Image (cartoon, rainbow over all chains, first blue to last red; front, side):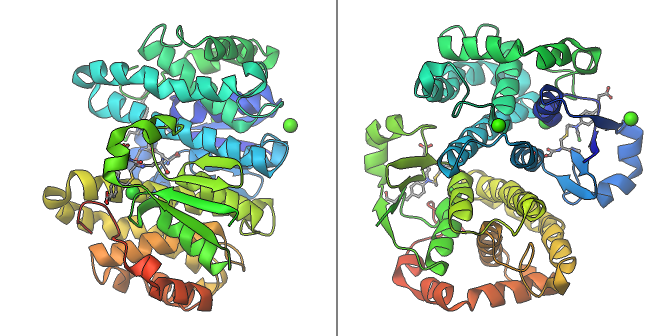
Length: 209
Length: 209
Ligand SMILES: N[C@@H](CCC(=O)N[C@@H](CSCCN(CCCl)c1ccc(CCCC(=O)O)cc1)C(=O)NCC(=O)O)C(=O)O
Ligand SMILES: N[C@@H](CCC(=O)N[C@@H](CSCCN(CCCl)c1ccc(CCCC(=O)O)cc1)C(=O)NCC(=O)O)C(=O)O
Ligand SMILES: [Ca+2]
Ligand SMILES: [Ca+2]
Ligand SMILES: [Cl-]
Ligand SMILES: [Cl-]
């Protein structure tokens, strides 16, 4: 497992998986796809769904951001202690994914006019993750069970990008707020989040956040 | 039965998990939610993400259609023979989910105006699945490896509904065509697709398909 991440110079759908790799002490290569390389058409045509990210783990080539996360989850032991927890881990991640889709649609298709409506709906969209925490060790460990899972990284990223979109959207949610604090303070992750590798990438591709 | 499906009276996002359960010889209870019951609001408020399907495996309550699929996939041994195969199964399922989201958006939000453009784009959206079949034992077995996985049931449902949307769409895709006929002829699944519990539900909820 030498790891490669093939993606545009943005945080987007590689942010969570980079946080996970960094926090887990994994080494990886960034293969940075410029607008020129994409436009030439060869790489795109070679991608299974015509999209990035693309990921290489030794001879295994993957596509789909959530597939990469589950693969890393499965192979690094970040997927709950048993089948019951693995199911709850999926349920969290599929929740994160649904909101990310709504986030991305707002960003890339309807930012100015749509933002009011999005932000009005946001407390209701965040509340389920507070609920999950309230029911797992009083919100003191992780989103599921007593160890970190790939869903924590993806939820973390969703929370961070939403604090940028709507400053203080976590204020009503003490468990969520504390959780962001705790996970962000994990020493290797902390270092990664403060690094120009992360800080100097835009969240999205169109200047909007 | 240990399993309960809680859903609207439609095939929709439950059609794949039902085929999976039937094909695997499992019993489950259908609990049907009517629009009136839904509009009352109390069931909706109790749902983690304000949506159906809801699934019960004993006291384990799940939301998210793909979470249900992955959970049954793990529990019933339909998730590849190893970690590399599990990753490829996720890759298929995430591709299936992406096209399902586009399909659902056509059906409920843009059917009249959008159908022609959608059908125009469809071969390009299906071809990745033909590609995967072509690279796995000549398309003669499953989507991944040599045993059925949860992603097969999902992919089958996606193919079935697209043959309803655009009859003959699989004429361009010999391996996908043979694949649909082959899985549909599996004796338990054949009986299930023939049965009233399947046939007497509409694909979607608004009269369009
Ligand atoms: N289900 C998939 C979704 C994958 C997905 O949506 N990928 C898209 C979205 S990726 C991020 C958006 N994007 C592509 C816009 Cl077409 C993009 C973002 C930033 C840059 C670079 C701009 C920054 C800079 O130049 O400084 C270029 C493209 C993609 O590949 N788009 C390109 C294409 O389809 O040809 C998954 O989860 O991986
Ligand atoms: N990420 C989730 C997505 C789940 C999802 O989109 N579910 C929706 C869509 S479910 C299918 C469409 N639908 C609900 C739209 Cl109101 C629906 C379909 C058929 C009927 C038939 C009613 C017949 C009767 O009442 O007798 C009614 C509603 C839902 O629960 N909507 C209700 C709501 O948000 O209030 C997953 O993958 O499971
Ligand atoms: Ca590089
Ligand atoms: Ca662990
Ligand atoms: Cl994105
Ligand atoms: Cl649906």
